[PDB]
Length: 97
Image (tube, rainbow, N blue to C red):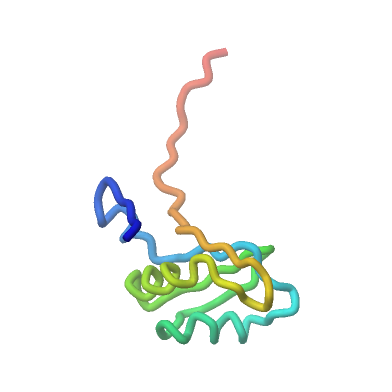
């Protein structure tokens, strides 16, 4: 049994959005909505660039999904999945010059 973790649960658990990269051009928002719907009642999907933006009712539906979906074959295309982290609080420092 392979695994790996570090830090805190709330850290990643805080994320409630999955970043699916490397999508298919022949596929449609319908298929992508049905591919994930099988796991849990989706929230909303959008086709943006080679990747897509899908929302879930909660984090439990995103993790349990991305967990298995991670490394799947859709429409004969290698689809990738990565946890989409927030922008966080980015401040501005000095420049000196």
